[PDB]
Amino acid sequence: VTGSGKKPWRQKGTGRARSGSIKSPIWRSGGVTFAARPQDHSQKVNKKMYRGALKSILSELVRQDRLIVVEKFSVEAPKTKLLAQKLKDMALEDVLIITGELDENLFLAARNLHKVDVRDATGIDPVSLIAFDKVVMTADAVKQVEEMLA
Amino acid sequence: METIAKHRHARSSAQKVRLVADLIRGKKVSQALDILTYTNKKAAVLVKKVLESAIANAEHNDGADIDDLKVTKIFVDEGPSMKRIMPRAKGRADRILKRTSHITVVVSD
Amino acid sequence: ARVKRGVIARARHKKILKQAKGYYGARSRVYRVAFQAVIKAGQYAYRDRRQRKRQFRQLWIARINAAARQNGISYSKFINGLKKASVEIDRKILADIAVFDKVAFTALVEKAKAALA
Amino acid sequence: MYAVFQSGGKQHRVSEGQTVRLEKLDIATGETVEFAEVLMIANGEEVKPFVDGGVIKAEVVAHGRGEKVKIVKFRRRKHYRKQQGHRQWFTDVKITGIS
Amino acid sequence: MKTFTAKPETVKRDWYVVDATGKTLGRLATELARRLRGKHKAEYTPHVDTGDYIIVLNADKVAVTGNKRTDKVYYHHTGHIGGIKQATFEEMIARRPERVIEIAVKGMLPKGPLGRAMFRKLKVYAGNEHNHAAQQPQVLDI
Amino acid sequence: MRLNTLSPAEGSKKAGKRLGRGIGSGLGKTGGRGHKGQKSRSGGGVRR
Amino acid sequence: PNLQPYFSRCFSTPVWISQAQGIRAG
Amino acid sequence: AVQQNKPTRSKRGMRRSHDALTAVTSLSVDKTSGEKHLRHHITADGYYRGRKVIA
RNA sequence: CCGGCGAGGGGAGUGAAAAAGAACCUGAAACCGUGUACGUACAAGCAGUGGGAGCACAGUGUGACUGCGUAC
RNA sequence: UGUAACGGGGCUAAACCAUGCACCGAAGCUGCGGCAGCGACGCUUAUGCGUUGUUGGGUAGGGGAGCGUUCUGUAAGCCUGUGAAGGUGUGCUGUGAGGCAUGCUGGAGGUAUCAGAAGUGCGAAUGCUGACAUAAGUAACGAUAAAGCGGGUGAAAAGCC
């Protein structure tokens, strides 16, 4: 705290409470007692705990029928209008698409749709496999995800 | 019809004004006027201005008929205090409270 | 996550000043005084739930003693005469009879005076 | 025509058509309840151990809880404080028979 | 069902008259305080004046046993630093013999506004005649 | 299996002692430290 | 002018250094 | 020379039981001008007891 | 309009709102008043609590008298 | 300092001694209702819940459970101008921290749930800041060189001219 280390009054004599800094945390406009610093809130996850979780989420998504496997999910033009349609016939509104290829046409077409997320089968995570109502995976993508979780 | 006149930030202290207000509480407004006229206080000159204004506030706006008016409510609140400094002996300083007040006369037929 | 505490300290203080209605002076207005007024008033309330059961038994026994002596016996001989007669009315009801139906008490005294002596 | 009976560890003196509050009897609301142990029936003529055949018969009205009591325990200067609330269960019975 | 309490309007105090000739003082004075308080009544309730009006007659003929006529001292203090005045029983019988019954009964009544009102119903007369013929006091035989 | 349905195992999270927070917590007015000595001071306590 | 442009804190403490007579021993 | 305990709202108003000002209620009418005035004082216009004194 | 060609106020008006009027969102608490109900001028003390009349309201408010009771 | 060496009044028994009986008397015991801990119970068939036994004064201190607040997710979800937070009442119910409903103000935001992170709860530190009391409408009004009048102006003049 910006201030001087001058003791505000003397220690004895004046009938005030004893103080020794204008920046003490008892005082107004000086000092947080245990002040924050920027910290790392990351946690360590074991790989067999991370892979055991994802194997246990994908096992539960076929239990509550929220995993739907497709064999291809592409869209011809990189247009949000077509994908907005690609999911009405599929009867989807809040969905996570997980593909194996690098489809940038499909990737842009869901960049504006809020409840639709497109991944690349390598960045699927805990919170994304849970916070979407349906998870739709292309058949080339579920081959890779089965592999990395052994 | 209750007719209010106020005098806000009256420069007399509220305890000094409340002494004069208890003289004209409930009196008929003609008898209340010459109680305040032969009362030798500074608050008597202040309160009489509000009562003479509530007398005209009644007969100009709400109606007429001075002679059946009565000082029904009369109450003095404490306004904001102006804080001043009196220097005392041996470097010491004190706080002077220039105490304002809020005089409210409610006249009523 | 700084937490300002003005809302829940107001409510916690207001809850205690509401329990201090009717108290004299600063015991109704000032929290520091009204807190230990309310804590003392709960302390007394605990104690006088014990003393209430004694003060009423004191009051019944003093009334049965008076109403027995109008019928010519003391409280001790009336209570001994009721126990030898196996009458199991308690002193709350024995005092209730003594002001409300006196002729139902002179019968109780007679049933005590008989089976005592 | 009043009588003395004894229900919830306490004794009550009731008359006809009077509600008396007792301790929480476990009989459902609306059921006739007998108090066969009647200590003293009185009238113009009085009957007092128990009576031989006088039965107070009542009719159960309501099962409530009482007005909340605050239990405050305090030990001054000894850093001890303990609050507790209490609502006591009762049973109201209207007296429909003095025999 | 609440326990009965007597009311300070529905209470009816009866008037009694007592001949205090030859009676032992504090044996007399404790039956007076019993009936001034109202403890002889089934309607007794300790916050209400439920007692009687007692007329004490021939107060100067009250008796004390032993040597108490010359040796019971009445100590009162006048608030000043000398203060401690004293009168024996026989001096108190000469000066104000009414005071002997009144002091003795007052120590036996409770202390407070109520017991000060129970003292108001004790009419103490040194002689043999009271003025309260109109209240028709029954003879109360001690 | 939604984000507002996941729970820890029972007993996996104990709370954590919060000291000096009143009479009911059992840790107020001394912080579990007892009365005035070296060990009840801030930073006090002898070396190993 | 009903504007209220008031003043501020406008000097510190002179002395609390004050009288000192009174003892029980020397 | 200084209090040991703050006096109350009760005792502060009990002291001012005698601070209450007393109204006049005794104005006197003048027998030639009808002006109300203090008793034994001249009027606002300078009449007194029927005579014009000051003007 | 009252006032001292004041200050402040009462109208009229603006506006959804002026109890948004500039000393201006919300407007708490201490603290200070006014009005009303009840209590209080023979009564002694941590001012409560238990009992409790009477009264005033539509259960609430007050609380005479009384037992116990020396704050944190 | 005032009885001041029964608590007092008072007592010749209302004092001692012996005997006997009754009664009073506590938060002890019993009755009645409730709640919790611990066991024994296979009583159940995760074991909750039941049945019985017994225990529940507590400082330091240890152990076990919670409450609420701000913030993140759940949340482009629900509530919300037909009235949010806040403030102020009232009622209801939880063993408690508390919770909910709502009348009035307020006039735009608030967050079930389940998790997550703590500037997470104040009556005290001769704590810190602001506000406001108290003494008290008291002390004082700062050289005891001194003022009085008549005009004037003014709403008002002991003080201005």
Image: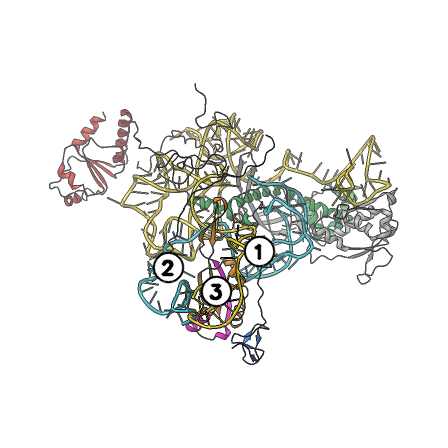
Chain colours: A red, B orange, C green, F purple, G brown, H blue, I cyan, J yellow
Hey, which residue is sitting farthest left in the picture? A76
In what quadrant of the picture does the N terminus of chain C appear?
Answer: top left
Which picture quadrant has residue G24?
top right
Q: Mark 1 lies on which chain?
A: H
Q: Do the residues labelled 3 and 2 touch (CB within 8 Å)?
A: no
Give the Cα distance between marks 1 and 2: 37 Å
State the residue in front, C31 or J2: J2
Nearer to us of marks 1 and 2 is 2
Q: Which residue is drawn at 49% across and 66% down?
A: B45
Is any atom of residue D36 visible in this view?
Answer: no
Measured Cα–Cα span from mark 1 to mark 3: 24 Å
Q: Which of marks 1 and 3 is in front?
A: 3
* Residue B46 disc label: 3
On the same chain, marks 1 and 3? The answer is no
Within 10 Å of disc 2 (Cα), the crowding (few <14, some 14-19, many 20+) is: few
- Relative horizontal placement of residue E24, taking residue C62 as reference (left or right): right
Contact between labelled residues 2 and 1, with CB atoms less than 8 Å apart:
no
Regarding mark 1 in the picture, which secondary structure is present there?
A: helix
| Boundaries of the magenta span | B54-81
- The image's mark for residue G1 is 2
Residue in front for this viewpoint, E121 or H20: H20
- Label 3 is placed on what type of residue? Leu
Chain holding disc 2: G
Q: Does the magenta stretch include residue B61?
A: yes
Q: Position of residue H4 (x, y in %)?
A: 58, 45
Residue H17 drawn at (x, y percent) = 60, 58
Mark 3 and mark 2: span between their CA atoms? Answer: 21 Å
Residue tagged by mark 1? H13
Q: In this view, does D70 lie to the left or right of J115?
A: right
Indicate the amino acid at tag 2.
Answer: Pro
